[PDB]
Length: 171
Image (cartoon, rainbow, N blue to C red; front, side):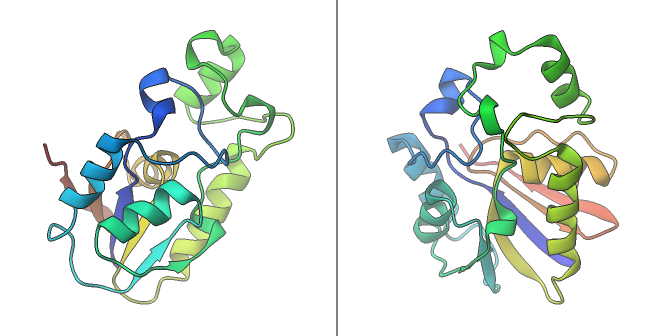
């Protein structure tokens, strides 16, 4: 199933290097610029989006009117929300780097996150554009056997659940 996953434009915590999960930060000026550049670069298909502000705003500036689904939200970092990556405890850095065994206090485990994301994608019965987050795109790319890091305001098209089709980044 052809699905276009879009990582929302940047927020302040991207440059600051802080874990950004359910903290509802707005897009920066550049983030909005990134979202606008996506207009005309994404296919005209039904759209879905995380209900978090940065994702919804990216969808809007990109020229879409998505149906909102919390299931597309970034992972809930719990007590680690806003934590500087730099000073994150080694056990957490390792869990996030290897994308396994991540259990943040008051948040979502990576296992629960993946279940949520993949259950949502399983429900996609037709091609569509999904406005979401870096962690979601990463989970998908990793499950398809590829490195999952992509720039803010960039997109990746996949043939779920088989392979990646294309990665699109604009300057």
